[PDB]
Amino acid sequence: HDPLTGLPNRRYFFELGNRYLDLAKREGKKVFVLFVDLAGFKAINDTYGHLSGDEVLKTVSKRILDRVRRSDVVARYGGDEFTILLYDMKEEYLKSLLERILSTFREPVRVENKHLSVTPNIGVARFPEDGENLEELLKVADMRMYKAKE
Ligand SMILES: Nc1nc2c(ncn2[C@@H]2O[C@@H]3COP(=O)(O)O[C@H]4[C@@H](O)[C@H](n5cnc6c(=O)[nH]c(N)nc65)O[C@@H]4COP(=O)(O)O[C@H]3[C@H]2O)c(=O)[nH]1
Ligand SMILES: Nc1nc2c(ncn2[C@@H]2O[C@@H]3COP(=O)(O)O[C@H]4[C@@H](O)[C@H](n5cnc6c(=O)[nH]c(N)nc65)O[C@@H]4COP(=O)(O)O[C@H]3[C@H]2O)c(=O)[nH]1
């Protein structure tokens, strides 16, 4: 597990997530893969130091975990990237999930009375439509996040 946030890492998101995809295949369920980029860590790190940036990451991680199911997967994909696997999702409920996830990551983190906030950008991929494996789905979600901010 990621030492800073305690969340599963990139390696673990795959080991876990690939099994969920195999389960969804058997159960005839859909799985939604969210790629979350957080903007604003460069400014926090440059101004206050990497340790304040790490406190922001830790609080944001805890907040997201508390707002998704314990059966869903939240991983620290990279430095300022998070990946979320939502098991047994449907298109009709997506808008509500995105609003909940965006509002949670957008909440300021009070670090010694300074109000530090990051800006989330989310890309979505859907299993089985967007791919057979988690590597494929993540690339689709990542590219969608990239193309929307252009
Ligand atoms: N994997 C995953 N799927 C999610 C998650 N959030 C919502 N869904 C999916 O979206 C459906 C509708 O969500 P809702 O509008 O919040 O509508 C929900 C909500 O109002 C309530 N609900 C169910 N569980 C919880 C919960 O643990 N906490 C809260 N506050 N409400 C819950 O019951 C309604 C119906 O729930 P469901 O039949 O299960 O139907 C849920 C479920 O299939 C999620 O965090 N992870
Ligand atoms: N709007 C909405 N939010 C959802 C949904 N599913 C999960 N969440 C969010 O994710 C948090 C953690 O879900 P959990 O791990 O299943 O942890 C849940 C779950 O174990 C249980 N719980 C609450 N409501 C339901 C429910 O309606 N059905 C079942 N089976 N369990 C529930 O209590 C724990 C804490 O619930 P919360 O405090 O509500 O905290 C929930 C809620 O903020 C949902 O379908 N709709």
Image: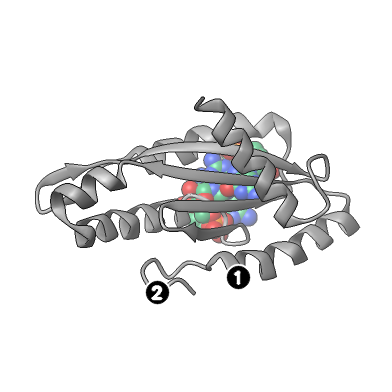
Q: Position of residue 139 (x, y in %)?
A: 67, 47
Relative side of 132 to 7, left or right: right
Q: Position of residue 125 (x, y in %)?
A: 69, 41
- Secondary structure, mark 1, is helix
Q: Amino acid at mark 2?
A: Pro
- Which residue is painted at 61% across and 57% down in the image? 72
Q: Mark 1: give few (<14), some (14-19) or many (20+) Cα within 10 Å.
A: some
- In the image shown, does 122 or 72 lie closer to the viewer? 122
Looking at the rendered structure, the kind of residue marked 1 is: Tyr
Residue 3, label in figure:
2
Within 8 Å of ligand 2, the CB of disc 1?
no
Mark closest to the chain's N terminus, 1 or 2? 2
Which of the 4 image quarters holds residue 147?
top right
Q: Going 30% across and 47% down the picture, which residue do you hit?
A: 41
Residue 48 % position (x, y): 14, 52
Which label sits on residue 21? none
In depth, the one of 101 and 122 nearer the eye is 122
* Spatial CA span between label 1 and label 2: 13 Å
Residue lying furthest left in this view? 113
Residue under the image location 83 percent in, 62 percent down: 22
Kindly identify which residue carries mark 1: 12
Name the colour scheme.
one colour
Q: How many marks?
A: 2
Residue 109 shows in the view? no
Q: Is residue 82 left or right of residue 27?
A: left
Q: Is residue 76 left or right of residue 129?
A: left
